[PDB]
Image (tube, rainbow over the protein chains, first blue to last red):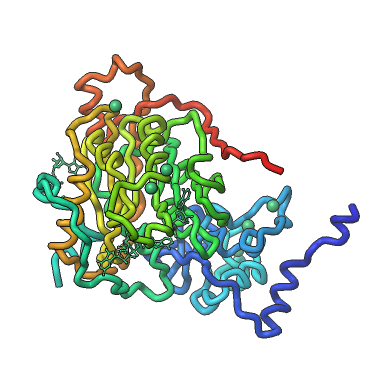
Length: 118
Length: 299
Ligand SMILES: C[n+]1cn([C@@H]2O[C@H](COP(=O)(O)OP(=O)(O)OP(=O)(O)OC[C@H]3O[C@@H](n4cnc5c(N)ncnc54)[C@H](O)[C@@H]3O)[C@@H](O)[C@H]2O)c2nc(N)[nH]c(=O)c21
Ligand SMILES: C[n+]1cn([C@@H]2O[C@H](COP(=O)(O)OP(=O)(O)OP(=O)(O)O)[C@@H](O)[C@H]2O)c2nc(N)[nH]c(=O)c21
Ligand SMILES: Nc1ncnc2c1ncn2[C@@H]1O[C@H](CSCC[C@H](N)C(=O)O)[C@@H](O)[C@H]1O
Ligand SMILES: [Cl-]
Ligand SMILES: [Cl-]
Ligand SMILES: [Cl-]
Ligand SMILES: [Cl-]
Ligand SMILES: [Zn+2]
Ligand SMILES: [Zn+2]
């Protein structure tokens, strides 16, 4: 109750850290792949298209990398054990991209970077 | 330029395995040279990708609900590049467990932190990958003798927890090696020492046991076979190459649906051994996979 009320806006803190000129989290594991994949955001195997890089999920998850509890139900990670596709233009900061962007529940593409359900 | 440059790496030729060399100091012409990797790709992602590309050419058993354990999976970066490559390579749904002396975050289904000697399991495994390396190996003060440490655990883990038909890939170097491990290679249908092309400038190799038979097929003297390995490396320079990393179209391990059966030690006849030797049979029960990490209780 009081422990939950205090907790720690880690997603908000990372955006402020970058705004202050902080160097983005490194050592995100980039995978070798064909780059002829579906282009969906989070997949069981690398699915990067010609405009994306595929990375090991756990290495791009702020919560996994910082050893802090996950917000998702019962601390369930959505990247661990999977592969996340990141636009080549934003591959310099995969942790920042996954936090600031959200996946479309219909086509499985990143909203604003592949989803065209409109 | 060399033909082997388009391969993921180079395996120890059979004639070098049949020699009786004395151990010599390893002296590589290109020692330490770094490979030219694709932009932003880590050395360990490239290395495991080439190991997996080579494993795709062997008769590996690939059963439904395959079980794979990866020792020495943590890096000084706090992540598991090799585990990410194994999970990309293995069929979806493959149970993948990894472990390391040091904490790290992984894509594996379960991760155990601590010395590999603290890892227990009643379950048998289909594939064992080890990248363990003792940093103290760099302190070459004495003669290059067989090393114990995690190697005694790996040998016992193979003899007790590897399913018949299963395979292993255990990392060795000039000084990080074990005679009993080489002797165990004679308990597989086939074996080799495989050198990744991205690490051609290192004495590193993966000792690969293909299709475990649970009995000696050939007698191997470990002290002689490691001397043979160093002689091969000292007389066969390998050109650094990352060419195989650019073609990932056939990368995923082919799902073979390999039969899984339970058999007493008296049911292992020549006909069963023949199926094990072709990657068409795995012998173990299909019970729940349970692992544990021994915790030492102190004040
Ligand atoms: C083969 N070799 C060994 N040495 C000497 O003997 C020592 C021990 O030799 P080694 O058994 O460590 O073998 P090698 O040097 O080939 O290993 P390398 O450093 O390439 O490491 C291979 C792999 O081991 C792992 N590894 C190495 N060091 C570490 C570490 N500190 N932490 C974690 N993993 C490590 C990595 O996965 C790495 O890719 C070397 O540190 C060096 O002084 C050589 N010297 C010359 N001049 N020419 C050689 O050809 C040569
Ligand atoms: C790669 N491999 C080699 N052998 C044995 O070795 C024989 C051929 O050995 P080889 O495969 O090394 O020679 P090849 O000329 O086929 O090609 P190379 O690999 O480029 O040199 C096989 O018929 C088997 O007896 C193997 N035996 C088993 N069971 N499994 C393997 O994966 C395997
Ligand atoms: N006795 C032991 N038990 C467990 N891990 C051990 C060990 N001796 C060495 N190691 C581990 O062996 C590893 C060698 S480096 C491993 C690199 C890793 N495979 C990657 O994908 O990048 C180190 O992380 C070290 O902690
Ligand atoms: Cl959590
Ligand atoms: Cl020792
Ligand atoms: Cl010991
Ligand atoms: Cl035996
Ligand atoms: Zn996470
Ligand atoms: Zn959509």
